[PDB]
């Protein structure tokens, strides 16, 4: 699922990001907006452009979101009970775009972190981002 | 997908006799029961919370019909689809806020409402030709999103 | 995940199938082969045609597979430990085609069972077929 | 996808300077580390079991290169792709047994090896144009499977 080594590889990477979590998370939000047209649809209220403090404000409550996901990584289901009772009841964001955002966070990522985003790491970061994905996704049917 | 002159006579022939009713609303009702996160574009209507009544539902049955009728213009123009659908592709983006994933989702369901209506008359042979059509429609509908 | 009602809706449906499990499962195998060209690729050894006792022989060890999945439905992970240590080590069948087979089993299904494949049922049958999917899929990364 | 005359000058301009080496083998090695079920079409080679050595790996680095070189004929012929790729689409089916899902998987990885090579030079603006290309390639490659 997540090996010690997974829980680990993940920690190096989520502590390089530091106080840049929502700097990155907002520029991952953006590229999804960018790369997939399709997803901008769960966002008709938002000022989508390079400007959008609706996106950075938005893009903060996300990485705020994953910062605290690294920390409560043994019990991911419990840490995310609310923030997935939210994705399911209300937002009802289709479980497909999650993979597009994880790849927009993943890349992100790569760019601000070239040296430390080894590949035993692009693999643990992909496991974490999928699990997060799966938790958020759960309370559906 | 440069389908037999033929699998048309069929993908057409099977289509003729979608008594366009029972059928559209069942695709409709089957979609908001099964993949329940599509009830999202649809509190525009009523009671979608126990399936006896999504089915039991008129606004659905009506919506149901309209989605299927507009699918049929597709079946009968399966050459240059992207064209037929162009305006509703254009409307389902800038007006409607539809997860274009929800299209691929409704074809998969249709090809199942169809499978159920035919039984033994709905083959292998025929399911391959409708899985050929459904995806075709979804991708003409899936178009002018920017 | 699976409500009492899920574990239930599922039982009616898997006991109508009866001694037709591998009759259906072989004609679900076939339509995947049929509908998706793509999947026939994890099968270059098999005589794919209407004939294939390689497909019915094959199509038996599958439904044999799901018959015993209805039964050990509380503990799906344990029942399927082997038959997913198999999908992961060896076969390494990409977690994508699982959704194509579930929809080829689902439809299947509909056809031999029109009356009893209500929709509170097409929804519990879809939950079961996805979970099965997820178990088989687990032992990957 | 009827891309700016422009985003070409770019999707081309960025491409020029894929020192076609370090790069292809990293896409290569990154794919069998991350999505490990692709090590399947590849015990044709050696030691793929600890990533220090998939990377550490020559047959990969070679395979790596050949996949990227043949991607480049794509970039430079991005009009009528389906054509360029037609023979290898034809070869990757009847000869090769490749999960065409594994193509979409290698573009996603590429657009990440690329993202990493450029950093700040690999934008929003540019990632949208490569996510436009990668999928294009995967679908020309994804073709004549029957
Ligand atoms: C890493 C993945 C995910 C995480 C951690 C996550 C987390 C969050 C959080 C923390 C919020 C704010 C909750 C609040 O308002 O109190 C939120 C809101 C929201 N999210 Fe998610 N999310 C994820 C994926 C997705 C994806 C991929 C989309 C869309 C395709 C999406 C769409 C939305 C929307 C529409 C809102 C509403 C915010 C608003 O009113 O503008 N989310 N999310
Ligand atoms: C085969 C697939 C689709 C076809 C051919 C189709 C067709 C149509 C048509 C012809 C209309 C009428 C619009 C007008 O008057 O010009 C419509 C409306 C609409 N559609 Fe689609 N549709 C498809 C899929 C979907 C899906 C999957 C969703 C949602 C899951 C959806 C949501 C809507 C909604 C919300 C409306 C407006 C209903 C209202 O007024 O409240 N459609 N569709
Ligand atoms: C309901 C879904 C799944 C179940 C229950 C399941 C179950 C099984 C079982 C019981 C076997 C036989 C094990 C044996 O030889 O001792 C097997 C083999 C195999 N399966 Fe799966 N499977 C599933 C999905 C898939 C999918 C969708 C594919 C391909 C896309 C696939 C490809 C294979 C292959 C290639 C074998 C090897 C059999 C042979 O040597 O011919 N499976 N599976
Ligand atoms: C951009 C994607 C792809 C391109 C453009 C590409 C291109 C090529 C080319 C040009 C060859 C040489 C064949 C010849 O001599 O005619 C080749 C071989 C081959 N490819 Fe692909 N390829 C792609 C993706 C994939 C993927 C994703 C897989 C596996 C995951 C794969 C597996 C193979 C294998 C196994 C060979 C033969 C290697 C050997 O001789 O052992 N390819 N490819």
Image (tube, coloured by chain):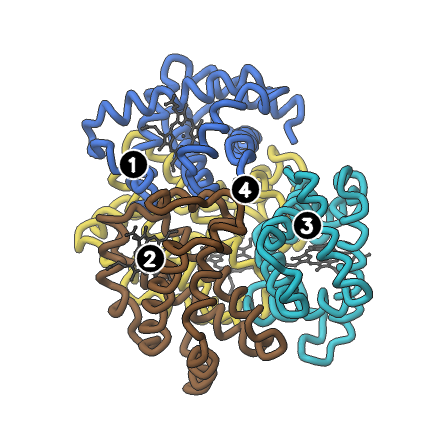
Chain colours: A cyan, B yellow, C blue, D brown
Mark nearer the viewer, 1 or 4: 1
Q: CA distance from mark 1 to mark 4?
A: 36 Å
Q: Tell which subunit mark 3 falls on.
A: A
Q: Is mark 1 within 8 Å of ligand 3?
A: yes
Q: Tell which subunit mark 1 falls on.
A: C
Q: Tell which subunit mark 2 falls on.
A: D
The x, y position of residue B136, in whole percent, is: 36, 57
Q: Which mark is residue A9?
A: 3
Q: Quadrant of residue A113?
A: bottom right
Question: Residue at left 45%, top 75%?
Answer: D18
Mark nearer the viewer, 2 or 3: 3
Q: Is residue B141 above or below residue D43?
A: below
Q: Is residue C71 above or below residue A51?
A: above
Q: Label 4: which residue?
A: B29
Q: CA distance from mark 4 to mark 2?
A: 34 Å
D124 on left or right of C112: right
Let me know if marks 3 and 4 both belong to one chain.
no
CB atoms of marks 1 and 4 within 8 Å: no
Q: Secondary structure at mark 1?
A: loop
Q: Label 2: which residue?
A: D142
The x, y position of residue D89, in whole percent, is: 27, 58
């Amino acid at each position: 699922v997540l090996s010690a080594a997974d829980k680990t590889n993940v920690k190096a990477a989520w502590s390089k990001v530091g106080g840049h979590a929502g700097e990155y998370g907002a520029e991952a939000l953006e590229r999804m907006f960018l790369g997939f047209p399709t997803t901008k649809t769960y966002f008709p209220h938002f000022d989508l452009s390079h400007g959008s403090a609706q996106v950075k404000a938005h893009g903060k409550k996300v990485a705020d979101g994953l910062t605290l996901a690294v920390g409560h990584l043994d019990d991911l289901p419990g840490a995310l009970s609310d923030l997935s009772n939210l994705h399911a009841h209300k937002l009802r964001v289709d479980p497909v775009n999650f993979k597009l955002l994880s790849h927009c966070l993943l890349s992100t990522l790569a760019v601000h972190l070239p040296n430390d985003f080894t590949p035993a790491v692009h693999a643990s970061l992909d496991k974490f981002l999928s699990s997060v994905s799966t938790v958020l996704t759960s309370k559906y049917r | 997908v440069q389908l037999s002159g033929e699998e048309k006579a069929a993908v057409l022939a099977l289509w003729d006799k979608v008594n366009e009713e029972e059928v559209g609303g069942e695709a409709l009702g089957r979609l908001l029961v099964v993949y329940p996160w599509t009830q999202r574009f649809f509190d525009s209507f009523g009671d979608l919370s126990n399936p006896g009544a999504v089915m039991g539902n008129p606004k659905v049955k009506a919506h149901g019909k309209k989605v299927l009728h507009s699918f049929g213009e597709g079946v009968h123009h399966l050459d240059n689809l992207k064209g037929t659908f162009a305006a509703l592709s254009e409307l389902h983006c800038d007006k409607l806020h539809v997860d274009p994933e929800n299209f691929r989702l409704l074809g998969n369901v249709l090809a199942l409402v169809v499978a159920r209506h035919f039984g033994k008359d709905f083959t292998p042979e025929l399911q391959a030709s409708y899985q050929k059509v459904v995806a075709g429609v979804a991708n003409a509908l899936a178009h002018k999103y920017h």
